[PDB]
Image (cartoon, rainbow over all chains, first blue to last red):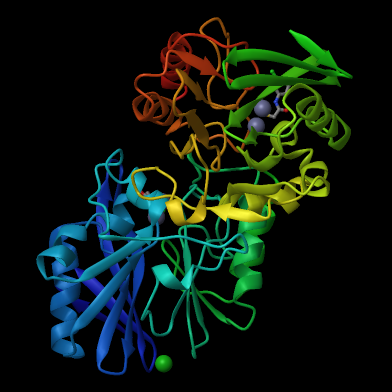
Length: 229
Length: 228
Ligand SMILES: O=C(CS)Nc1cccc(Cl)c1
Ligand SMILES: O=C(CS)Nc1cccc(Cl)c1
Ligand SMILES: [Cl-]
Ligand SMILES: [Zn+2]
Ligand SMILES: [Zn+2]
Ligand SMILES: [Zn+2]
Ligand SMILES: [Zn+2]
């Protein structure tokens, strides 16, 4: 089940994959959750997304030390919002190499985020350029197009049932997408469907703001987005 | 100004011309879109197609008559019809084409033909040189999301000119025309980033207004401020 560790929650999703969850109180609504991933790749660990804060992200590293006890080789962060990049300092303090879409790194200062140390770029078909994502092990990074934000990226976990949609995808029980002025409401639906088509064998869809769901999360999200066009 | 068919050309500098093409639309009437033609030694470089293949062919035929140098390459500045509607005409003329990778990704969704090559950008917005080989005086800058997620901009080295494409409107414009693909959170910062990337440019060229001073940048950013 869910393992509590400090103020975070960790859930094993597969033999080599865990979901990290961190919480932030907002005005009028407490304990807004955000999820990321932790992946064991042989003798190293890879992280997808920080927690909301530096202190919480340090607790992710502490949990990894206690439960996995392998070095964290790198982290990928999936766009320039606080839930995904708010804890970059904890990673850099620990010497962990960080990667984000070049556009996320360009947006980070405007958003009050610390940029990742390396930039990912993408082919016209959305797949990460290998020269920018060397030695990513099972992390298969895909840029699906603009949607939740212009910079949002997604990550398949090779060999598992799992694909991570980040904040682009919401579960099949969602009532809305959030989506604000930095959403692209013209392309959101196609971007959500492109994520599904990029990871056609994924049966467990992991998301930032919902618990894991089946592929219906992708379809339901796309159908909500269709109505915004 | 000179005419070739349905196209209008205006020389802006010794080696730079603006091309203007028109598409009839309900209510608006004829809608102008501007791009650039740059003479770089023994070759010509193009920024943006016209709205259609046939209008883009008219650009190329005017170049052959007026300049009579081969067109080496074209850069197109986002995946909307005014900027990429004529890709097939460029390709049929043997012209190598370049666009933001994201523009090429969006082009099929938009009913556009993708460029042959994709540009990618550093975290500071400047094009990665390995993706923009032999661009001569064209200095390509991604200012951030604004008019669209993929909009790019181009400065012309050796001149006072910077091209804002559809991101920038002139200092008399009343609104930005933003649709669902605009990023209204970042638009203002992206407009200002374009200005800061080309801080010495005194002639700002843009898609839907005649050339203006840097007041186009300031006014665009201030209009965008109000959408946040
Ligand atoms: O702050 C962000 C960045 S995606 N998201 C957010 C905020 C409040 C509630 C929820 Cl469900 C998501
Ligand atoms: O169609 C496009 C793509 S940016 N722009 C357009 C359309 C109508 C009027 C104006 Cl002034 C610009
Ligand atoms: Cl596993
Ligand atoms: Zn977000
Ligand atoms: Zn989020
Ligand atoms: Zn446009
Ligand atoms: Zn336009």
